[PDB]
Length: 319
Ligand SMILES: Nc1ccn([C@@H]2O[C@H](COP(=O)(O)O)[C@@H](O)[C@H]2O)c(=O)n1
Ligand SMILES: [Cl-]
Image (cartoon, rainbow, N blue to C red; front, side, top):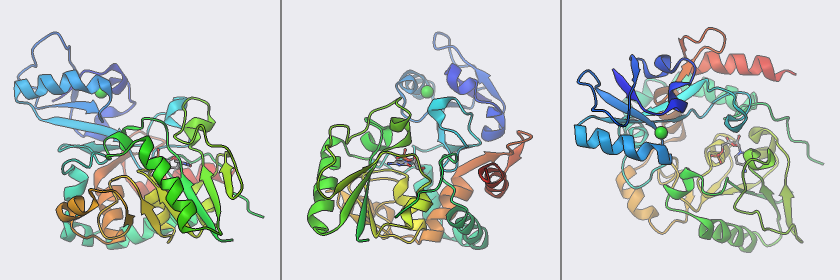
């Protein structure tokens, strides 16, 4: 079956329902058993490197896991288990350097066309139901040329493997201010940073003149309703802004950039766009949320689907 080296992965409740194959615990100090057909690791976490090297030396395929795009109520850093995982047998969605399984699913346009009705339905529920990767934050309350600038957690692997770093956050903020000289600039702090368990790229930024720091945990769709445009490096927020109908400028190379839907500023955007080609928003959504992500039922733990997870999350949110 699938070999697992990381105790953290092994402890994910209902892991075998996400992987849809039996899983077995392996030792880094013993040969890979013959019955193991693939090895699973978590993204590019440092713990992945040695299992990946073993897999390659043993001729076994590598599967990289990560959290789903609609994951849970509370944050991962707070211990809440995931209701959704991505399962990538090629790379990982946030690594722009080569195709990922997600990239290939987006490029399979016929497969995505078959899911247009499901995609439209789920997109509508996510936007109008105010859902996101995490789902405990209250709705934002406003009181209007507003430009949203999205911070991330320092050294997020989606930044590093998306060909970005501190420089792109500085360039992004400078561009937002220079390109919108009369707007209010809202810098949104990431919730893991608000929880105190991480630091953000704008940690040293002084709230100043036209720049307001949004240091509150609020649901993205509710906040996006009040902004005119969104600047990101690689945050999932950028895709959520596309769902909300807002223009998105991208300074890194996230999974949703370079398809023709974003104002891409990264110096390699032309090269990534040549590899990816074009895709529509509904194609990207179907590939990412309906084909790439896998779900369990929040009440039974059995294999499930996005619609059931959305239905349950909106239950919990009505309070
Ligand atoms: N500045 C930010 C960055 C992320 N987020 C939340 O964190 C989720 C994951 O975003 P990242 O990809 O930036 O980690 C988003 O879907 C959103 O719910 C936020 O609310 N404010
Ligand atoms: Cl790992």
